[PDB]
Image (cartoon, rainbow, N blue to C red; front, side, top):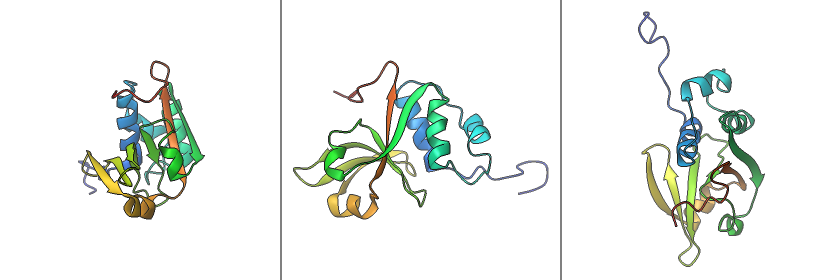
Length: 142
């Protein structure tokens, strides 16, 4: 709206959200308001590079790299599968035995288990690996 009350609808951003989840997953601070203020200055969502820097600014380690689904089982989970369409999601586990993939839906704020055909249909090859000074292993949910 525009009447000195809302100005601009807080259009949710899966990217920023994922950052929050990952930031919170690592127990690292994250101010989406400030994040968007620093990286989403455009107000159109956190960019790949802007998002990566968003996590770094939080004293949180992150790095986008082109990996293969077969590698996601060895990458730093939970990992963030960057989606050029903005419909990203956080990979937390992969059931190669069943070809399924456990991801965190940034829309519903809940985990989900996709099928290879599904994950493959969504995966692009570029994933963002996150790490924290205190958590540089990823496997926090032993």
